[PDB]
Length: 227
Image (cartoon, rainbow, N blue to C red; front, side, top):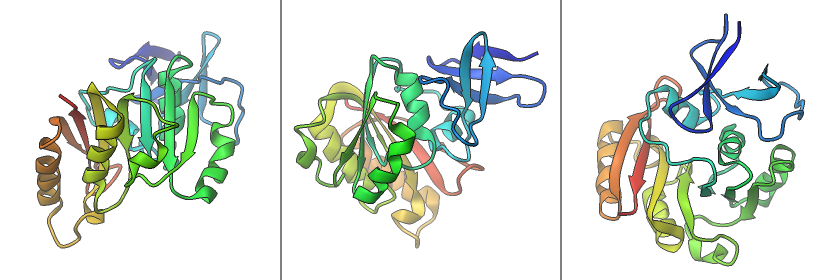
């Protein structure tokens, strides 16, 4: 029998059937999409979408035992790098209609190609912008509860801090997925992560740091709070 139970984190579920067990999922905000290749489980009249850790760094973090997950129902999220993977759809499922997600990408082409994935998920607002210059989209993005960032750039920690200074509420959280080689290919990943932690700690309280292996190689997710 198929059993869908509530995960520790609200909006997240643990699906345990006969074959696909030890798998997490979110409740589809827009059931009936019938998107080519969708992996959905119908349970008690509702659709649950399998969260693929190979296609979502947040899914990987949760499966790796993430303890702090600030993205919850009703929260507002500034999402830098919204087009990568399947993460946006799951964050949309979790936040629900009472919340909102402002997604930033620098390429108009990337945003245009993102249309078919978010067109029905009206709680996602795609916005063109350069994440290194947060001030440029201040008229569109409000103060938010959480900033989630997946930007493989050398200055990604500074990007988080600068965006937090403009948009993050006091007490709000930041979540950043860091690819060590996007910062320094000449240093050991653990050293890069330690340096990133030092940089973030000057502005935030660093709450948690978790490696994403085996789903990603030399990537770590940091959860921080704007004290």
